[PDB]
Amino acid sequence: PKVATNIMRAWLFQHLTHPYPSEEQKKQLAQDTGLTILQVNNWFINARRRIVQPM
Image 1 (cartoon, rainbow, N blue to C red):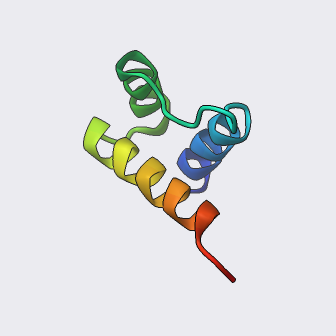
Image 2: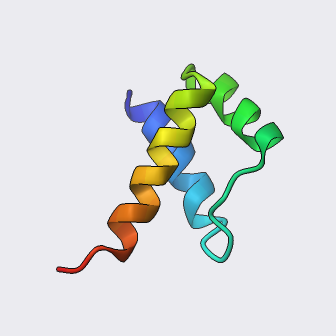
Image 3: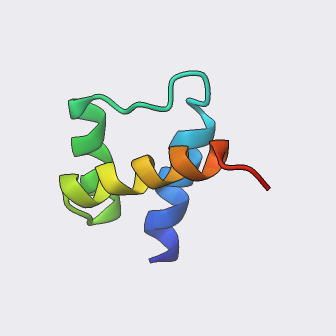
């Protein structure tokens, strides 16, 4: 769980200007994390929603 989260957090911070992984990138992250494409996409939707949310 921690490893998977760190994989996607590292990718996110390396792509803050365009935090939208392509279909191929989603497949790479799913392989590295052990998550499905659906789960990977959900994690990034939530990440982008929480970044812009107010305090």
